[PDB]
């Protein structure tokens, strides 16, 4: 919805909405923190899709209010005043809102005001799943969470563990950094490769049949929308890198077979299967904070039937998986994303980029995202919708 | 139940007339063509008086921030307004306009 | 003029000039420092209404020149060179100017230049009153200083003492916070309230009609323009803050009654009387430096009949009033002003703000300022007025 | 091409191109470093005319490649990977280019890619002369280096030594700071003046014949274009600085006669003859890095007939000329250039500046530069030239 | 081989494009401008887009990915970001049948 | 006192002629249609020669920064010029152009 120069949008006819979605897609669920990070009665702040939000846990349930008073637009979080269990009072003129529905229920500075009961602060649905806090940054009653999650993430036996941080790049550069079969060249020296004895080529190149390697999913019963890049089953693993015909670098000839298939799903979550070990899966979100930043929400899933396994998995995670994979492997993806910022900062990169074969899957994602997103977030959504209808 | 606003002829089409009520919030009577309508005078977006606004057809634009309402349904017509305005029943009898004491 | 999106100005029909006055009002007197801060032959720099200025004291009298050489536009203050008592020579090409009228009287690098005596550096009137330095940031002959000062500030026996600092918020946010009848809520825990046994409600339940909420002064004997906050005339003070009918906070039940008289005056100075003690007054200016900052020029006045009383007052000021009131009370106003920056930084808050009853006082000020200001400062005044035939 | 507001360019009919050339002139040679600073197989990064470049030395010869991968536009220099002697491999997806012609010769992650051999990274000619590295930031076959160098710089026996650094000001402010006969007023207290017994007036003012003092050169056989300000033979040295007829400052009455003539040449190099000693010459470039910065490339030349004379000059350069002249004299020029930034930052300074007689030479330079430059560098050149059929 | 059979001249309306796939080689694109026929590589030289999926405006083909364009007669770039010329293949009509060269022109 | 400048026909309509005066600042004589006017030649904003500028009607545009003046009143017509130009009455008699020696 008009976030980019019109001259540029007219040029990218195949995926203009995607290029315009600089602030992310509205009306989708997004993970922003882990359940253990938000305690009972201790509001936490965060910015999602450019909007400042407040999250609080009351009687164990999470509630989300926009962190901007309706009166003079100050953030309530500058000085939090929760005077009753179910409400929050602005520190300025004491306009008081209910966490459950955002209604302005009282105003301490003028209990007779005509505004009481007649105004409502924006609220957003919040749901906890797999120890992760998801916020529906949208309007109207929310769709089921599964619609915006990759396959198997919500499986009963699937134990989820991970980490989250803020990275300085637009969310799309992160998505395309993750859903890229040839970028793993940057991970050729990661400690996970040797230390976990992985079989990892320098890159996965397009196999014989292109129509078989890329699988667009828009028929999932759950409503999921995404694209598969079947690199393992239809791609070609390049293990020997040559220059002028001379081998200058080789891939990893380990025993553990990983990354059989990768898939990217709206609103922007990647699934790598299996990874970082043959018996695990990696699910990572690239959540838009503002046009220049995103949350890099990493999670690793491993089936567990009992606490003894869960505890064992949790122990391995802290001692190996987190330090060796999430960090040891993905840390290079961080500066890689930061390195693409300049080229796309003026939006011109969306026109001047020179793609090659392995980027076919990314193009498929751009079209899927353009066609199936549930809304283009705009700066007007951030400040206040504007219209003369 | 009904208050005498003014003579239907005292209002030129496309004009607004504020109606103050004793011990109560003021109302706004609009004449769109040959029909009359009424809503609360105070804009739902703040403390502005709509009777001091500008009427364009059946839409009243608030003088403070430019928000607007359809005077027939009281529904928001322009941002930043979002809260429906309270509408009051109006009736013309013997050339004189009357407004209901309570919103319909 | 034309400092804000025309679409926004068209929307705020009640006070468009005020919203447009992002850089302040031109052709008004503004206090910028205290007399004791500038000594004989020691030029001082400062920025007022976006303009860099130089102030010097020669033979006891103050003079103000624009701190921008006519030649290549450098600030003369980068390397001050006052080679004779009545002039200042630019450090670059030696263009020399008279402090008295700003005339280019000499050019050391070209004594016979035809530009000599044909160009003039902008000068602004400067006046000292009550130990304060006021600059008339405007054109032509200045009006009496009395026009731009609150009643009684210039009274013969009024002893004025104060403090000044740079605050990071647009000047208007500061003005409105000061004149805001309900913002008193933020001062509920001030040390001044308890330590000086002040009576301080949390707010007011308005009484009477809209017209009775304020008293607009369109003309004084000297042409003053201002508004008095009369919310306490027919309004009910709120001492018990409730939420859902339950008491969650109470005002201060002190015996000392202060601030019974509150008025804001163009170009932007508040008068609170009496405050912070029954026998004194507070006059404070919110002076525009640039679009994002202002001078918070605070003063406290107490009538004194002799040098003994003035000495005693000076002692009380330094040991009690300054730390307990000017800082202990008003420091909270400082961060409150800063908290409103984001909402208005894109000029959207001037459209989206949801006001309530006590804001009648702010609306009256916005209208008065819009109707009686002596000119809108523009970036063009800063760089150089532009006009093409 | 549209680097500046058209309204402003239309106002400066005498030198619009010059005012538009905020990023510098394309299709000219520019010195960017000294030869001893770039070693065999040691890639070095730099920004010239807004473009990020990579320079490397292979078998002694210098090569220049645009530091931006054709694929996703990242800077190859983030993680330099020169797998083979003649190439550099992007750290991201491994696209590989030849330093010699910028041709994409290999792709380690997809050796079968159809892009191989059909894409080419931008390359720029590089030439080493007098121990200085010159890059032809232009397109097509380059002209002789001599065209963009001041007279005598390339003389067989001229020994060149220098220093280079990045200064925070647009290159034109630097050019006009150097080619300005009156600005030397700022150097009146330089240690060089007394320590090298120089005869230096407060400024050189216009003589009785302007057409004789300024000499526009556009008939040079090597094609160089420039302007001479014959301050020594046609100008008037001002030694007594007066204010109101009284002497407040005098120049230096040393014995060494320097600065007989100054000349500025496209693309932007000044020649001061003789300086800083009667038997030496100073040649300095103000190289555009981006719109706000430039390389201040200083060189001092002194004829030397053999290695003994060269090593002697080198020792004198390090012990005297560099600290006393290049630094002791020109250091004041640095903050002087920074001081002009504000006035010209909004491009308004090019309209509001008030010139005087001595600026006549600068005006001649602006005209010559507008008329004989070989191209206006634009932001589109930096991001990627654009054109619709 | 030398001349590849494409289709009947009448099977193409003016202003249309037809993709010609080839065994073991890159695809071609045949364009009909008026009653004349031209042909170039099908793959845009700026990336991986298929020009046969673009839009023909006279004798200029516009790539659907980034808006680049080429003159179908000369194969020269007509709009940025395209800079590399397309290979052009001769087209001839034999007894109402459209044939495209198997090898591009050398120049 | 008056200074004989030139023959009226020596100047084509819409042109400007610089008139030098030894020991004094040069003047600029403008021919607007068949009328003649005069002012100081030096722009009041710098060192530019107005005689080298562009005449549009009765307004001369400085060639340096686009400043302008009305050649009849000498008053600024366009920024950055702020200081009024010196005006010299011109008189045409028997086809000869004369300009006052002193600014009046
Ligand atoms: C190909 C192979 C592995 C990966 C990939 C693309 N993208 C990834 C993102 C996170 C973790 C692993 C991978
Ligand atoms: C006049 C006289 C000397 C100099 C000058 C102008 N410009 C200069 C720049 C560098 C070094 C010396 C000079
Ligand atoms: S800004 Fe929150 S109550 Fe006024
Ligand atoms: S008060 Fe009516 S639009 Fe704001
Ligand atoms: S910039 Fe001040 S004398 Fe030149
Ligand atoms: S960004 Fe360089 S090979 Fe992909
Ligand atoms: S692929 Fe054709 S313009 Fe980029
Ligand atoms: S010198 Fe005439 S407009 Fe500046
Ligand atoms: Fe990665
Ligand atoms: Fe306050
Ligand atoms: Fe200098």
Image: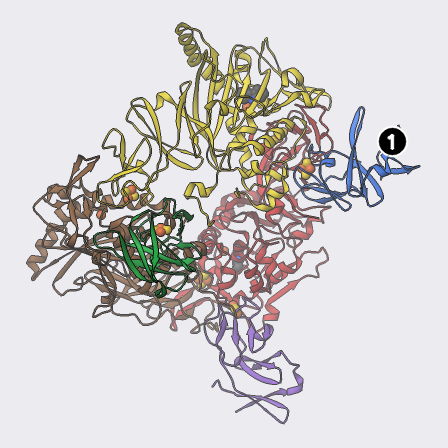
Chain colours: A yellow, B green, C brown, D red, E blue, F purple
The answer as to whether callout 1 falls within 8 Å of ligand 7 is: no
Q: Which residue is mark 1?
A: E5
Judge by depth and name the residue closer to the eye, A388 or C150. Answer: A388
Figure check: D113 above or below C170: above
Q: Looking at the picture, how far across and down is residue D344, in whole percent?
A: 49, 56
Q: Looking at the picture, how far across and down is residue D204, in whole percent?
A: 51, 65
Q: Is residue D272 visible?
A: no
Figure check: A28 above or below D150: above
Q: Name the residue at 59% across, 68% down.
A: D213
Q: Is residue C217 left or right of residue A344?
A: left
Q: Looking at the picture, how far across and down is residue D148, in whole percent?
A: 66, 52
> Looking at the rendering, which quadrant does residue D134 occupy?
top right
Q: Looking at the picture, how far across and down is residue B48, in whole percent?
A: 32, 53
Q: Name the residue at 35% across, 47% down.
A: B85
Q: Is residue C296 visible?
A: yes
* Chain of the residue displaying label 1: E
Q: List the single residue furthest toward the bottom.
A: F94
Judge by depth and name the residue closer to the eye, D225 or C242. Answer: C242
Badge 1 local density, few (<14 within 10 Å), some, or many (20+)?
some
> Looking at the rendering, which quadrant does residue A246 occupy?
top right
């Amino acid at each position: 919805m008009a976030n980019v120069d019109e001259a540029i949008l007219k040029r990218v006819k195949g995926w203009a909405p995607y290029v315009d979605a600089k602030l992310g897609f509205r009306n989708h669920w997004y993970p922003v923190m882990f359940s253990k990070e938000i305690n009972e009665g201790e509001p936490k702040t965060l910015k999602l899709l450019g909007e400042n939000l407040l999250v609080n846990r009351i009687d164990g349930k999470l509630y989300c209010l926009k962190d901007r008073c309706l009166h003079r637009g100050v953030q309530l979080s500058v000085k939090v005043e929760c005077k009753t269990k179910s409400t929050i009072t602005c520190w300025y003129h004491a306009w008081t809102y209910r966490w459950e529905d955002g209604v302005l229920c009282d105003i301490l500075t003028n209990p007779t005001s005509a505004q009481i009961g007649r105004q409502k602060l924006k609220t957003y649905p919040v749901q906890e799943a797999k120890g992760c806090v998801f916020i529906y940054l949208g309007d109207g009653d929310p769709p089921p969470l599964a619609r915006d999650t990759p396959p198997n993430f919500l499986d009963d036996d699937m134990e989820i563990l991970g980490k989250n941080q803020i990275i300085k790049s637009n969310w799309r550069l992160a998505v395309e950094n993750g859903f890229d079969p040839s970028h793993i060249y940057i991970h050729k020296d990661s400690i996970l490769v040797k230390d976990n004895d992985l079989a990892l080529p320098l890159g996965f190149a397009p196999g014989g049949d292109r129509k078989q390697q890329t699988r667009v999913v828009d028929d999932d019963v759950v409503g999921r929308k995404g694209v598969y890049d079947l690199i393992g089953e239809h791609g070609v693993p390049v293990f020997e890198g040559t220059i002028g015909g001379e081998v200058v670098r080789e891939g990893a000839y380990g025993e553990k077979i990983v990354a059989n298939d990768i898939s990217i799903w709206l609103p922007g979550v990647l699934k790598v299967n299996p990874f970082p070990n043959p018996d695990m899966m990696q699910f990572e979100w690239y959540v838009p904070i503002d046009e220049n930043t995103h949350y890099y929400f990493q999670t690793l899933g491993k089936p567990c039937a009992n606490d003894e396994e869960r505890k064992k998995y949790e122990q391995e995670f802290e001692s190996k998986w987190k330090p060796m994979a999430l960090e040891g492997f993905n840390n290079d993806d961080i500066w890689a994303r930061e390195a693409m910022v300049d080229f796309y900062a003026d939006d011109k990169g969306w026109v001047n980029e020179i793609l090659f074969e392995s980027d076919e899957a990314i193009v498929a994602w751009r079209k899927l995202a353009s066609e199936h997103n549930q809304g283009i977030q705009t700066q007007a959504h951030v400040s206040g919708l504007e219209h003369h209808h | 139940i009904w208050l005498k606003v003014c003579a239907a002829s005292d209002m030129q089409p496309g004009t607004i007339r504020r109606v103050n009520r004793v011990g109560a919030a003021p109302l706004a009577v609009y004449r769109v063509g040959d029909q009359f309508y009424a809503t609360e005078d105070t804009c739902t977006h703040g403390i502005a008086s709509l009777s001091e606004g500008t009427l364009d057809g059946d839409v009243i634009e608030c003088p403070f921030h430019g928000g607007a309402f359809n005077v027939c349904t009281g529904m928001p017509a322009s941002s930043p307004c979002t809260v429906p305005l309270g509408v009051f029943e109006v009736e013309v009898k013997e050339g004189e306009v009357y407004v209901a004491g309570e919103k319909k």
